[PDB]
Amino acid sequence: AQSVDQLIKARGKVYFGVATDQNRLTTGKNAAIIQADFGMVWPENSMQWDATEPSQGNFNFAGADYLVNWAQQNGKLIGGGCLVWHSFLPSWVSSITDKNTLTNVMKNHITTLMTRYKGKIRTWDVVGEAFNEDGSLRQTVFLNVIGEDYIPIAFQTARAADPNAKLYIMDYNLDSASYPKTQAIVNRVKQWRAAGVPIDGIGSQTHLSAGQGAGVLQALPLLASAGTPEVSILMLDVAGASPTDYVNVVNACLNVQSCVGITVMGVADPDSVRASTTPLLFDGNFNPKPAYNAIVQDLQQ
Ligand SMILES: O=[N+]([O-])c1ccc2nn[nH]c2c1
Image (cartoon, rainbow, N blue to C red; front, top):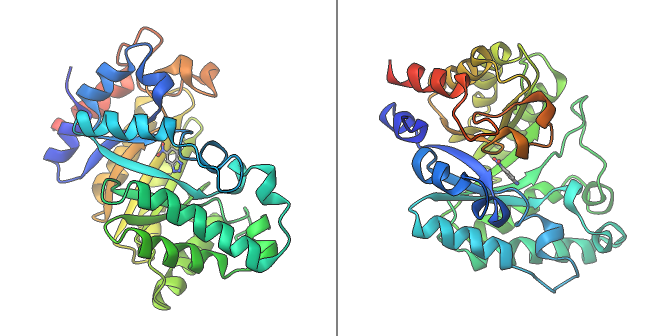
């Protein structure tokens, strides 16, 4: 059984990665599969805001430290995130109505996480899910209280905290070139970078239904046209796990020079949030599914 990470490196890419955390690494056969087959790990939950700063200035790094130490011992690259994401905010953040207060809170959260792991993290997802489906900016507490400047502020703060890390904006429903969100993230990233905002990458949080892989072949080149040094596929899963969809996503990555790699949402189907759709690359016995073998064969050829 061949390693997709090794094979994608042989094709000139950086990694094939996976999301995990302490719970997964101590159960099933997740650790053994990650050791063999994946070259980068991301914390699924242990670096989100609610996990790391459940009360203001009272940080909890136990789960994140476990992941980082496991990755270093096993020679894996590490991704971290998401530093600013409305979906994982504790209530103490959402209640803040004062611009200066919230700006300092946000800067402190960013700097504290990034400093702790300085030099050890390849990629940080700095801002997540900042766009509405129509391409307008999502009206989260950060937009409502700080305004549109919160995104530049987050990236400039992140660059200062660890200049080694590649800083990404991420979003979902960027899977079709003509979708309004895809157009808008491309346009705004172009503008931010032209003003000197340090956005190194766009990460596409790719949750596909059956048959949607084909559209990624056109959407990913469009995302790359924003001119960031890197793009990536993140959080990848596919309802039904058809080889056709998975191979299309891999081929999109191969066709886009700036696409550094792909991260899947987990290891085995039963641990998915949509397990009924069996959307991952390993089954409930931890055997590689037809889609895994198809990706291997595509990368070997
Ligand atoms: O690619 N990922 O699986 C992944 C998981 C959780 C994250 N939080 N921020 N960015 C993330 C990427």
